[PDB]
Image (spheres, grey):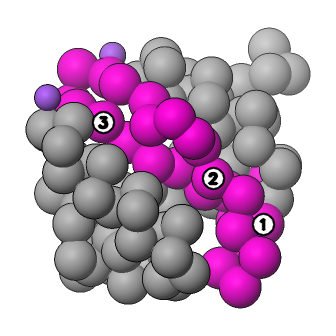
Amino acid sequence: GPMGSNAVKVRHILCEKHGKIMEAMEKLKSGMRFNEVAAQYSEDKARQGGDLGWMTRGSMVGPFQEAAFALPVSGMDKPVFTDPPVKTKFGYHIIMVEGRK
Ligand code: NA
Ligand code: NA
């Protein structure tokens, strides 16, 4: 149905280990731009600054999806990201959303 048309343009930092995602979180809280944190730490989409692009409802792993649709759109000078990190079967994610449908 209608909810299958919902989507987010989403960016993340993924780290298997909790200690490393915590290092990434500290960099965000120091003011580092999200894409630069993703380049330093992410194990997915690092060469894209963490950008996953547009993702439709159903296409994201469950805990990620719930966290992502809960975030308002933000930009990387004024980011709104998940805190605490979100655990999935891939590891720990810090997520921000740059577009919403
Ligand atoms: Na861990
Ligand atoms: Na999961």
Give the numbered dot on residue 63. none
Residue 60 appears in the rendering? no
Residue for badge 3: 92
- Mark 3–mark 1 Cα distance, whole angstroms, equals 21 Å
Mark 3 C-beta closer than 8 Å to ligand 1: yes
Look at the picture and state if 68 lies above or below 42. Answer: above
Look at the picture and state if 21 lies above or below 59. Answer: below
x, y (%) of residue 48? Answer: 33, 78
Instruction: Please state which of residues 51 and 15 is positioned toward the viewer in this rendering.
Output: 15
Q: Secondary structure at mark 2?
A: loop
* Residue occupying the point 47% across, 17% down: 62
Residue 11 appears in the rendering? yes
Three-letter amino acid code at the position of disc 3: Tyr
- Mark 3–mark 2 Cα distance, whole angstroms, equals 13 Å
- Residue 76 lies in the magenta-colored region: yes
* Residue occupying the point 75% across, 43% down: 71
x, y (%) of residue 98? Answer: 70, 65
The reply to whether callout 1 and callout 2 are in contact (CB within 8 Å) is yes
Mark 1: few, some, or many residues within 10 Å (few <14, many ≥20)?
A: some
Quarter the N terminus occupies: top right
Specify the segment rendered in magenta: 74-100
* Residue occupying the point 22% across, 77% down: 40
Indicate left or right for 90 with 31 as reference. Answer: left
Number of callouts: 3
- Mark 3 or mark 2: which comes first in sequence? 2
Residue for badge 2: 81
Mark 3: few, some, or many residues within 10 Å (few <14, many ≥20)?
A: many
Residue for badge 1: 74
